[PDB]
Image (cartoon, rainbow, N blue to C red):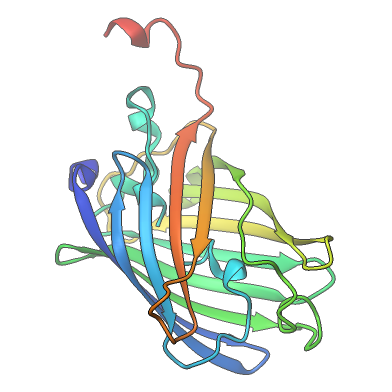
Length: 233
């Protein structure tokens, strides 16, 4: 079924339209995903000029179908099971002592390309806070995010805390509440409780004048006891 679409390297397109305290922006990303290795490589451009929020605060918004699920966990991979029809991914991201993002994305195949199309609205931010004031370091801590099935909506949900490094040495909490539900009507896998382990490397393209982010990301599923029965099938 859907997971057969990810056995090779798959081109990715990301399109985001954002509006944070009335500061509007657009981001376009392109690259490729290698779910066999759990690997994503993308370059993102702010096509509207200057990004009015820090690039790290957008990493989680800017394709969990590229996670590497170990063989003994292939039956808990909701994200690939919804493909190619796709899923809707919705989040509220509450920054502590600051504003919040609300995001709605559609992740689905358009032709041969896996497309992530996002609408983001940000509200109640401090114009001199860590977000609109650009006081966050250009990096992304490694992080584990717990997945649970949402049977009553036929999808998954997850809540997790992102800890952004502030340039003074403090930490800015971004509390994520996330919900995913399939777009099509076909069968989806509802996972047992598990987590995704994520690492992110952020860099710059020397030849790129525009405001941009080069991202390498690894996502690997874990947390389901690989017992001795699975070692004999």
